[PDB]
Amino acid sequence: SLYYEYLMNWLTKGLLRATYGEFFIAENTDTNGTDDDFIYHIPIEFNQERVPAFIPKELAYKIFMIGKSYIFLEKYCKEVQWTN
Amino acid sequence: SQDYCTMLYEWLTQGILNDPYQEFMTYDDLERAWDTQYFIRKDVLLRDCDSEEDKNLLFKMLRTGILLKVVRASLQIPTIPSNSSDITIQEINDFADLMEGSNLELYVDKCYSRANEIFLKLFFQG
Image (cartoon, rainbow over all chains, first blue to last red; front, side, top):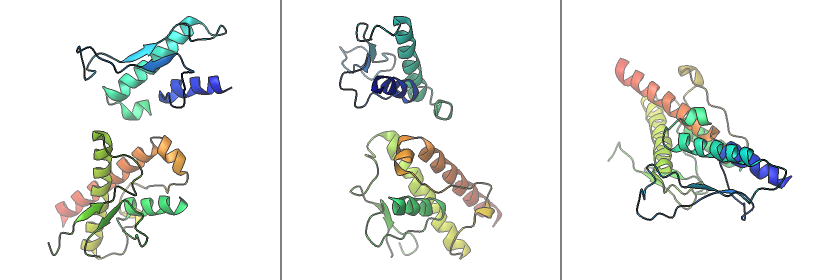
């Protein structure tokens, strides 16, 4: 129940609060000097083995891409109304 | 927070400042002779107001309130009726929902556009 609730929250608002390491998509702000201000880095990471067996890896990748594209539209394209 | 939502709605729709308990996040002086100073209280704020987006949002809300109060003082009216423009703002009911959703931003943008349109019309026709 709470797992699907967190999936819903990430897929809708792109939020990862109160996760406590119970999700497979996170943000990695560590930078080695290349694109420190995240002009093109897209510092969103997605783990593989953190998903259960009843969910396809393709579906997990699709969820990760949905969240990444939503954050991209909300941050870089300024499409506030459409994203909302 | 039913009182806080009503106070915020009044400030964003009419620019009327009534803070007898020092709870609202903005209050003006003269409670230089005509231009009063608007002080923002960060201890009673609703957000952090540290990022550029939040700073611009707070500045937009303050500008809306200032324009509403200036229009009221120029027209010598106690309040600005909603029929003076084509924009109507709905009162806030759920503070948690307003904070978690972009409905706050939508209402703020709508009231700011209404205040700017009214100010431009007044200063252009009168």
